[PDB]
Image (cartoon, coloured by chain):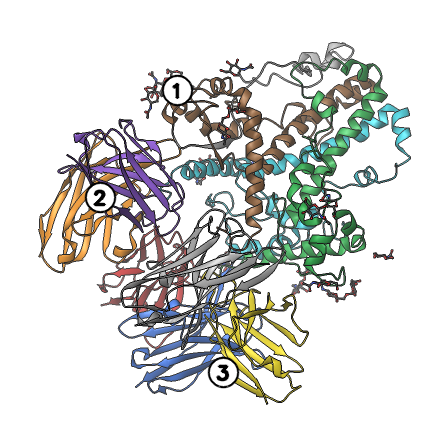
Chain colours: A brown, B green, C cyan, E blue, F orange, G yellow, H purple, I red
Amino acid sequence: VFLGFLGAAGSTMGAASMTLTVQARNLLSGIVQQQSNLLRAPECQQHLLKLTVWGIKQLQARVLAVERYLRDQQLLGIWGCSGKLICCTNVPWNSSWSNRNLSEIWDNMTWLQWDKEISNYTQIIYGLLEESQNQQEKNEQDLLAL
Amino acid sequence: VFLGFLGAAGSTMGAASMTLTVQARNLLSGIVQQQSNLLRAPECQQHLLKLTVWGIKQLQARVLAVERYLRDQQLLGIWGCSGKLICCTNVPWNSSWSNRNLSEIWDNMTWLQWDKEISNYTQIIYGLLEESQNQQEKNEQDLLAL
Amino acid sequence: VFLGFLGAAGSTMGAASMTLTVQARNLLSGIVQQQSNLLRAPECQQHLLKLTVWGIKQLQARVLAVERYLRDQQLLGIWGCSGKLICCTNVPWNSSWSNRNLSEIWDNMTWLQWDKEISNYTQIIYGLLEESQNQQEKNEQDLLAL
Amino acid sequence: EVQLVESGPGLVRPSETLSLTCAVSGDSISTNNGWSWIRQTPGKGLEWIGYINGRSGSTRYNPSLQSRVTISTDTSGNQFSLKVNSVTAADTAKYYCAFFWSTYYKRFDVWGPGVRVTVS
Amino acid sequence: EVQLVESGPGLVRPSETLSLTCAVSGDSISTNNGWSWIRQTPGKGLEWIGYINGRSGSTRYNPSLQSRVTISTDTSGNQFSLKVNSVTAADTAKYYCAFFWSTYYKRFDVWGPGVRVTVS
Amino acid sequence: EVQLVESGPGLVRPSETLSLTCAVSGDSISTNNGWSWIRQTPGKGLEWIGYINGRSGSTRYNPSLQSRVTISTDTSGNQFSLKVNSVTAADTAKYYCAFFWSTYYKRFDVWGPGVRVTVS
Amino acid sequence: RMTQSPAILSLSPGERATLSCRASQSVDSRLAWYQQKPGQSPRLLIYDVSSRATGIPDRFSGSGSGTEFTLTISSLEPEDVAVYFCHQENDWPWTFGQGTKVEIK
Amino acid sequence: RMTQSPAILSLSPGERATLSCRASQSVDSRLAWYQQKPGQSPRLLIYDVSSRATGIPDRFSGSGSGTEFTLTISSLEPEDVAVYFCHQENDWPWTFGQGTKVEIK
Amino acid sequence: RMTQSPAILSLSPGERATLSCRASQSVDSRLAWYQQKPGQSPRLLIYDVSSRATGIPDRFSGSGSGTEFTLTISSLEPEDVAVYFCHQENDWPWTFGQGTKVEIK
Amino acid sequence: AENLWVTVYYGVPVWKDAETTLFCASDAKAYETKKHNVWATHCCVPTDPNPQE
Ligand SMILES: *[C@@H]1O[C@H](CO)[C@@H](O[C@@H]2O[C@H](CO)[C@@H](O)[C@H](O)[C@H]2NC(C)=O)[C@H](O)[C@H]1NC(C)=O
Ligand SMILES: *[C@@H]1O[C@H](CO)[C@@H](O[C@@H]2O[C@H](CO)[C@@H](O)[C@H](O)[C@H]2NC(C)=O)[C@H](O)[C@H]1NC(C)=O
Ligand SMILES: *[C@@H]1O[C@H](CO)[C@@H](O[C@@H]2O[C@H](CO)[C@@H](O)[C@H](O)[C@H]2NC(C)=O)[C@H](O)[C@H]1NC(C)=O
Ligand SMILES: *[C@@H]1O[C@H](CO[C@@H]2O[C@@H](C)[C@@H](O)[C@@H](O)[C@@H]2O)[C@@H](O)[C@H](O)[C@H]1NC(C)=O
Ligand SMILES: *[C@@H]1O[C@H](CO[C@@H]2O[C@@H](C)[C@@H](O)[C@@H](O)[C@@H]2O)[C@@H](O)[C@H](O)[C@H]1NC(C)=O
Ligand SMILES: *[C@@H]1O[C@H](CO[C@@H]2O[C@@H](C)[C@@H](O)[C@@H](O)[C@@H]2O)[C@@H](O)[C@H](O)[C@H]1NC(C)=O
Ligand SMILES: *[C@@H]1O[C@H](CO)[C@@H](O)[C@H](O)[C@H]1NC(C)=O
Ligand SMILES: *[C@@H]1O[C@H](CO)[C@@H](O)[C@H](O)[C@H]1NC(C)=O
Ligand SMILES: *[C@@H]1O[C@H](CO)[C@@H](O)[C@H](O)[C@H]1NC(C)=O
Ligand SMILES: *[C@@H]1O[C@H](CO)[C@@H](O)[C@H](O)[C@H]1NC(C)=O
Ligand SMILES: *[C@@H]1O[C@H](CO)[C@@H](O)[C@H](O)[C@H]1NC(C)=O
Ligand SMILES: *[C@@H]1O[C@H](CO)[C@@H](O)[C@H](O)[C@H]1NC(C)=O
């Protein structure tokens, strides 16, 4: 855990796609989330009760990490990707959002650069992914299929 | 998000089944759960620390939304529906719980009316769904299958 | 719910594998997590606000149950088991971790005894399960498959 | 509610292609997937030929005719048709136009009267 | 632990149906899925005929006999049987009753001595 | 970038096994899955024979040759080969060595010049 | 992939008629029955083994699972002379049984 | 499992050439086209119905889905005399169409 | 779908005997071996390529994967004269190889 | 223009500038026995176990 947490950040999209579990494992487990799960009492805890302001700040940090995690999982579920780090969809690429070939982006761009190129199309793409899944379920409820 | 949140409430069960992502998206995202995830500090936060009672009420609301969400997801997992908004099971309908044909309920009833008709059979049905999944796993652990 | 919560604890691994939903259902639902979800206000709540230390202790207990649940679910997701109480993997057994035949462990050992026999190989096994899933995804991204 | 009306040659010779059509009245064939052809052969009974999905144009054909039959639509005429290549005496049968609705909520068929086709 | 005992005609004529039975001693056939028939044909070797699931009555048959063989049970007699229709000389073989246990935790077989059947 | 060079007998007699090899230059065959054989038969056109996965040694063969063809590798020689049993006149064709790369990110082929084989 | 039996029944008015149908493979619960009167195209009677089609008399019923199915007509009427067909709905080939006749005397 | 049409086209230089290919089963979007000049092994032109292979002139394009596909060569040049093949990439058998010829006069 | 080789081995007592079996398709790790002595029904020796069945001598072992498998008998004894069979457990047809013989001289 | 489709990836190494609350920690060695030290009481979470970089 955290042995190369953002190690692929400067690498290409292709190479970086091979380290996806590395970042996923660090979204729900900060130091305080490890101390909170010791078999022994952590001892510190009395401090956070005697002084309730510190107790509240710690809980807010823990609750937020959980809420952010769950929201990303909910979107993957809605889009039809329950689990999987990499999933294919039926939404075609518009070639307006970005107009580059596969041999250019997977080999020459980093994920940070990509993110800064299509950031204002994010909501359009997410909207289409949701519509696609709804259409798929409508087709599933037809026993003659395709 | 929230552009027709309960819009299908007065519609029939059939039509309403086509809007399921609309309600699902609003279970983990109230206004305070959006403000809490800004890149900038929300600014308000000092108020909830200076006066710890308000800080606690806000956390209780956030924790509860998460617990309710997770409990529903756990039941779907137990019943054998990981993900999916609509899933088929192997539990037969009893015709005691409700005794109507498909052409009557999917076209003439709303979900609110349905809920008020079979509410005291809810636990029986949930119990059967769990038993069904356990039986399925017992059959899966047999390499000769069916 | 909780009608035989650890009832299989003294039973063999084989028999105990048939009660897995029994323990799973009790990880997110303690008494306070039921009182918190009443349609009526619980009434007690004012106590936990007037005296903020008790309010904080209760939230810490609730947040922790959620964090522990989610971490186990994240590991199952990473290892390629989204949902399911029982899942097969591609990691071979080393026969160093434990060197017993199937007819000995499934019929004569309890899960507690097993846990005390291979506890210091837990991290090795978990590491291998993650590597296996990453290798599987690398193979999936090849349209000629196997 | 729809009505299905078949029409076509009542006689085809060996190795010729048989072409039958079906008009649909009361609803559209650009949608309502499940437009199909069924064959009733004396001495064999009923079998499927195949069907078409009006919304996408995709088709499925019973394997026995996988290399012999084409099903397509005329959505302007709101009619659909069946063509079977290399027709032989063994293909003499009563041919039917049918609409099969099978979903999670409803099940029904509509059948036309059919066309009897003699094959020499 | 079970014992399997086969019995039946050692001679069947062309186009007749061959009927062999197997008694099961030591356990039940209303459960314990995996009751099966195996054929050993000189010049070909071993092949499966098919098997039955005592708990549900469902069966699976090797495709070569998909249209020829029926397997069923007599749970009162705690015996099961095999019937093969339209038997010909090519079906002369040694037939066996077997029990196959294959689960996540155990693997084993029990075989009976079998019946040799001559086909004219 | 690789080069593929085929070699083998230009003549095989009835019921003999035909053996063709392909050398690979520029990359390894112990990896890079998708090493394959393609056949071009005058009067029929192009068809696949099958392919091998250099990383695991597994193979897949077109069903028409499921019982007739073997594909394997010599990773030391960095060459791979095709053997087709019970070759007949109907198998006269132009045989090719090819490399097919098909992933989520890239698609390309490399073809060798091939070997023309006459079958008596 | 399904066979009906017997080829024909002959019953007195008001008598109960039963027809069997056996599958070569499991068809789960996906079985439909049809009624074809001479000069008519087949009418759907029963779907999913026992559900009545809209407009079907309560004389008609049925049961079965996997591979073993039965069509039953109680209180058989003269208007029920027809050829009854067994239809597979659990797989792509959708085969039909050969059709059997029931005649009222 | 796919058939090309016509067997041969004959075009004037600069004219646009079109070739069709029909599948017996859906091939989704998994269709490739190849160019085989006499004495040569087939060259990949187009993959996934409309994506050009590296090094392919913009004269080449295509479209289609499911079962109905077309290969188009605009501004046809004498260097394009070749046999063009339709290749199925949506299933295991990977069949090819028979190949059609385009000749420039 | 599997072929054994050679048809027969002839070994001195105490010598190690090896038999191969090749699949036409991958059988994963689902391979079993059986021993049939004359007058007997086949006995299970090895399952899942290398796991010994209960009651089997340690003379018996094996290895292999995918399509290439071997059965080995070390320290071969006269009581091991038998026909050995290769059994596919990775698919529905469950085929067997033809059976080979090992004889001790 | 290639015929491409949207693929969703999770666990991508991307970030944005942000404000948040850090929780503080200390090296629980000599400082652990300070007892009445303010900083040793507040920054209670143990850290610096040969920390990663
Ligand atoms: C940082 O950038 C350099 C330069 O582009 C990358 O260097 C490549 O490393 C691979 C693996 O050793 C070689 O096969 C390439 O030939 C190198 N590129 C060049 C131009 O020489 C380096 O990998 C990048 N860092 C990370 C983490 O990806
Ligand atoms: C509220 O009730 C009315 C009356 O039942 C619904 O009106 C139907 O609307 C559809 C779509 O325009 C028409 O095809 C039907 O013919 C209308 N029904 C009648 C009796 O005329 C209306 O849709 C319902 N509201 C919602 C949100 O579903
Ligand atoms: C506690 O241990 C006893 C003794 O091993 C278990 O008793 C077995 O119960 C089953 C079911 O009734 C019988 O089929 C076995 O024959 C019994 N064993 C013996 C040696 O007689 C008992 O089941 C165990 N408790 C639990 C919860 O598993
Ligand atoms: C492909 O793009 C077409 C043009 O859309 C325009 O540009 C995009 C980037 C947006 O700003 C949009 O509001 C503009 O109208 C669309 O008409 C077409 O639907 C797009 N296809 C898909 C799948 O999204
Ligand atoms: C079908 O219903 C049968 C009758 O059960 C009775 O009515 C229901 C509503 C409950 O109140 C129950 O306690 C009563 O005994 C059951 O015996 C049968 O098991 C039911 N089938 C299924 C699948 O639940
Ligand atoms: C099988 O075991 C081999 C020996 O590993 C040694 O013992 C284990 C228990 C560890 O303590 C390890 O650090 C030792 O080196 C391994 O070399 C081999 O990789 C193992 N196979 C698998 C799948 O893990
Ligand atoms: C949308 O993103 C592009 C990225 O290249 C940027 O240049 C453009 O200014 C952005 N549009 C707006 C309104 O900010
Ligand atoms: C059970 O639900 C029905 C709904 O129609 C209601 O009439 C009945 O009174 C309920 N039973 C009890 C004990 O409340
Ligand atoms: C590892 O676990 C075994 C369990 O049998 C135990 O005997 C051994 O002492 C443990 N090793 C260490 C270093 O604690
Ligand atoms: C459903 O029940 C209603 C009320 O008895 C009836 O009018 C309707 O025709 C029934 N539906 C079917 C398909 O029989
Ligand atoms: C992708 O675009 C670049 C820049 O125009 C070009 O050099 C490269 O050859 C293109 N890739 C392909 C496969 O055509
Ligand atoms: C498992 O090991 C025990 C102890 O050595 C032995 O008695 C038992 O027979 C073994 N099981 C099998 C299937 O060989």
Q: Which mark is residue A108?
A: 1
Report the residue marked by disc 2: H100
Is disc 3 in the same subunit as disc 2? Answer: no
**Quadrant location of the C terminus of chain I?**
bottom left
Q: Indicate the amino acid at tag 3.
A: Ala
Report the residue marked by disc 3: G7
Q: Nearer the viewer, mark 1 or mark 2?
A: 2
Query: SS of the residue at dot 2?
Result: strand
Q: Are marks 1 and 2 in contact (CB under 8 Å)?
A: no
Q: Viewer-proximal residue, C113 or A111?
A: A111
Q: Residue at x 36, y 48 (%)?
A: H91
Image quadrant where residue F110 sits: top left
Whole-percent x, y for residue F20 in the image: 16, 46
Q: Are marks 3 and 2 in contact (CB under 8 Å)?
A: no
Q: Indicate the amino acid at tag 1.
A: Asn
Query: SS of the residue at dot 1?
Result: helix
Q: CA distance from mark 3 to mark 2?
A: 54 Å
Q: Viewer-proximal residue, A126 or B48?
A: A126
Q: Is residue G57 above or below residue A85?
A: below
Q: Indicate the amino acid at tag 2.
A: Thr
Q: CA distance from mark 3 to mark 1?
A: 73 Å
**Quadrant location of the N terminus of chain I?**
bottom left
Q: Residues within 10 Å of mark 3 (few under 14, many from 20)?
A: few
Q: Residue at x 68, y 32 (%)?
A: C67
Q: Is residue H17 above or below residue F10?
A: above
Q: CA distance from mark 1 to mark 2?
A: 39 Å
Q: Viewer-proximal residue, A60 or C53?
A: A60
Kindly tell me whether mark 2's CB lies below 8 Å from ligand 11.
Answer: no
In the rendered structure, the answer to whether residue G63 lies left or right of residue J37 reads left
Output the chain of dot 1.
A
